[PDB]
Length: 50
Length: 51
Image (cartoon, rainbow over all chains, first blue to last red; front, side, top):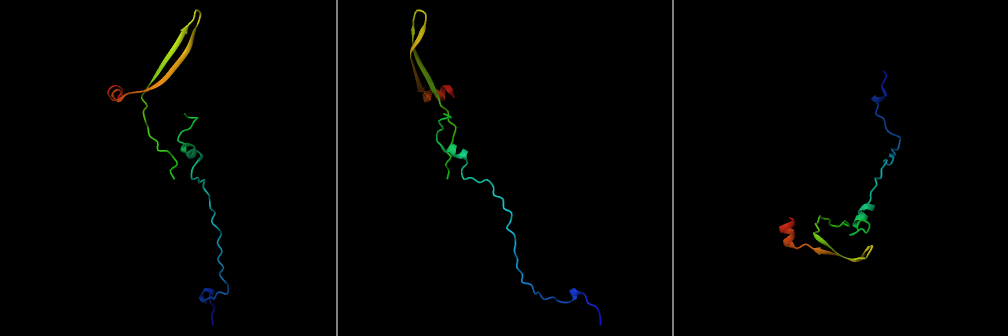
């Protein structure tokens, strides 16, 4: 009768779709609640400075 | 939490009053006492004179 392209025929999927994605490369910045400085400044007086 | 102190500029007006007692020997001079005190500057002197 005639030739037919593959895309011309609907295809049913025999594969189970298992979607696994990698974990995003995540960069941890230096985060400090109080720096050694803030902490040194937290003192009401510094004997050294005084 | 704000562990940092509240900071502000101030101005200290005071007079360093040094009374030195000196003994004068024949060939030398010696301090027999140095009283150092810090006196407040009165308001009438900070407002009228200094400022």
